[PDB]
Length: 279
Ligand SMILES: [Ca+2]
Image (tube, rainbow, N blue to C red; front, top):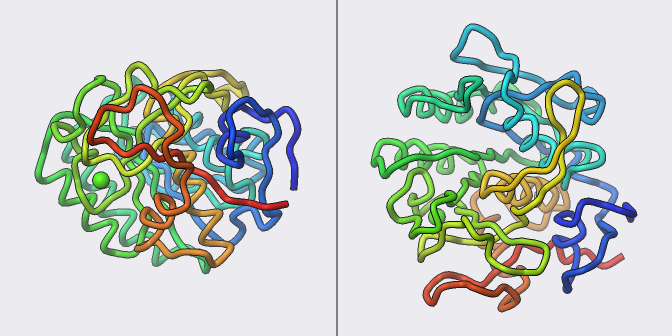
């Protein structure tokens, strides 16, 4: 399949080169997979989700996304126009309030929730969780992310926007999950992206157009926007049978475009997420 005039990041993830504008992907499009977006919520009624989104949990007085961040991330996973995996099922877990804040105890509970809740959902091709959130190092946050992964979910987490080594942030620093850095449309590391040995992969993160609340769209930047490209990629590859939840981060690194990014510090991987789709 080909989507013309796609967001640059979708075109990037199906290309060996920067500077193209068509997204190429197998038509299976993540059908029969599931992706949990653990964030400020998802506006499930947005036409871009086509009835494939729902809220499954909140820790606040509403499950509505009163921020937009979670809706944007969900859209990069799985919206019809803006998404990597255009037929995946999306499940929202609102651990962040409408200011985008959340206590670590709530975030942990939401990760444990997903590990159980997958057993209540139909995801024959596998399960992914996208965590576009983080704060300072916490062994308890990292352990929650490790349990989610161990339970059979492909966990993708943002590296963070501090232009610093991700070893000092959680859940970015957890070794067993897939930690995602950000790039821009000229294959530079994004100015804000964290780096370090704990990174596994980079994805498009500067000037990413996706869904927003009120049935809208906008472009924003962050490791939070790189993470759902990887999460959606994982769902897409699992639907194809090419990998599993336990092996997908390694598969994505194995199959990534290598050596193409600039301003990568010595000791950080130079790997850009790529679907290797041959039309
Ligand atoms: Ca990691």
